[PDB]
Length: 224
Image 1 (cartoon, one colour):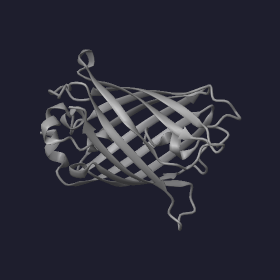
Image 2 (tube, helix red, strand yellow):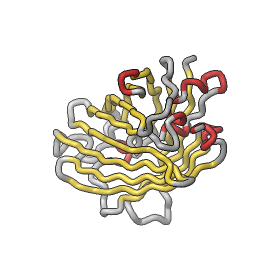
Image 3 (cartoon, helix red, strand yellow):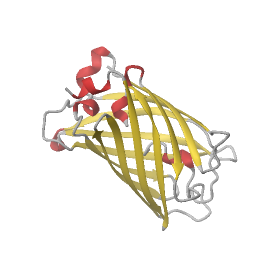
Image 4 (cartoon, rainbow, N blue to C red):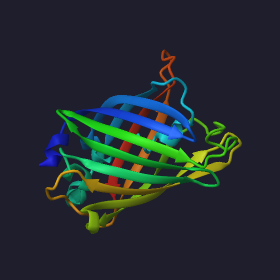
């Protein structure tokens, strides 16, 4: 029944509250998802002023229910099967030689709108590292999200790496560990091992003076 909620274009709202090394901030996002094409278009605004971390480091945190699952893999789509009640998504994100983010999000429908409500806590960051020093390029990210079942939680786990370009030509690795658990008590689809091929293009609205990010993203399941 959850998959039927994604056959057309679905409005998306994202709300994040964060604290990284004591720097508190909030982000609000709005956009649309079209799972038929695995396509997401969103604009995010820092509602508290200036974002204290680089926008690219928040992309993965800021709705994998919008993935395009090929017909032959649709029985492996945990994310839609949890809807409309939703799922809790938790991550730890280890920035190599720097701090970590720990995130908890609730992803669910509020009426016809798919909502991603997030809390983010970052600790152990270096004052003059790539994150708090804002040394990362405003650059796209792309990678594969490796998904496995977590029967014990009636959910899934995932792992993946993001390579963020640094301004000097080097790379800041962000190792992601993820867990998803359903909010409701209904049956869900527990998948065989597979991946999500994900690509995010980042841009700016030339007329927008608030600190913000425009995002175009494609997400497609594969590996079966």
